[PDB]
Each structure stands twice: as structure tokens, then as C-alpha cells.
Amino acid sequence: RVASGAGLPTSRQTTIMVTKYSEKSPITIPFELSAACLTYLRETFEGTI
Amino acid sequence: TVSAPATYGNFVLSPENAVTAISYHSILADFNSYKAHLTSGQPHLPNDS
């Protein structure tokens, strides 16, 4: 604020309080695995080379 | 009383057989013996796979 001449009006604003709300925006992405991939990953046959 | 084999024999793919199975969809058993005879110039293998 600027202190002014006694005849000019003015205001008493020292502070004001303002609230901001968070804006939500989720993201997503898929990835896919085949049943054969899961079989060979999980069920490790002793088997061969 | 006759003498009989006590267990099943084991047939194993060599790593060259892995490469050629993946690439050419085919196997040549005893790949390395064919290889060594072919480079040495010798026409007869001692036995089969």
C-alpha cells in the first residue's frame, strides 16, 4: 500500500487468503504377456538347452 | 539269464542343434562330428546318433 493524502480515501487490506484446488489427471498404459511367455517364465522345466 | 540295459539312453541336442533348430527348423544329430569329418576329408563316421 501507499500512504496518501489525508483527504484521499484508501483501504485497509493487509493480506488476503486465496485457495487453490488441485486438478486431477491420471494416466495409464497397458502391457501384454502371452500365455506361452508366462508358462516358460514361471514353469521352468529342468529339460534341455 | 541275459544281460539287459539298466536304463534308457539319453539323446541330447548340442548347442549347434539349438541354433539350427531355431533358424532352419531342422536338426543334424552329431553336427560337430559331421563337421570335423567333412573338414578333415574323411568319408566314414564310426556310428550314428
Image (cartoon, coloured by chain):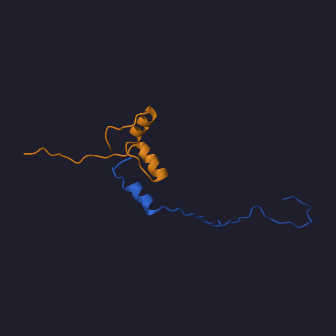
Tell me what residue is drawn at x 36 percent, y 56 percent.
Answer: A43
Tell me what residue is drawn at x 28 percent, y 46 percent.
Answer: B10
- A12 above or below B18? below
Q: Is residue B37 left or right of residue A18?
A: left
Residue reaching furthest top?
Answer: B40
Tell me what residue is drawn at x 41 percent, y 49 percent.
Answer: B27
Quadrant of residue A15 within the rendered picture: bottom right
Tell me what residue is drawn at x 42 percent, y 59 percent.
Answer: A38
- A6 above or below B47? below
Along the line of sight, which residue is nearer the eye, B43 or A13?
B43
Instruction: Locate the N terminus of chain A by quadrant.
Output: bottom right
What chain is the orange one?
A: B
Q: Is residue A35 left or right of residue B46?
A: right
Colour used to depict chain A in the structure image: blue
- B47 above or below B21? above
Along the line of sight, which residue is nearer the eye, B4 or A39?
B4
Image x and y of residue A7, in percent = 92, 66
Image x and y of residue B46, in percent = 32, 37
Along the line of sight, which residue is nearer the eye, B41 or A39?
B41
Q: Disc count in the image?
A: 0
Q: Is residue B37 left or right of residue B8?
A: right
Image x and y of residue A35, in percent = 43, 63
Residue reaching furthest front?
Answer: B43
Image x and y of residue A49, in percent = 39, 47
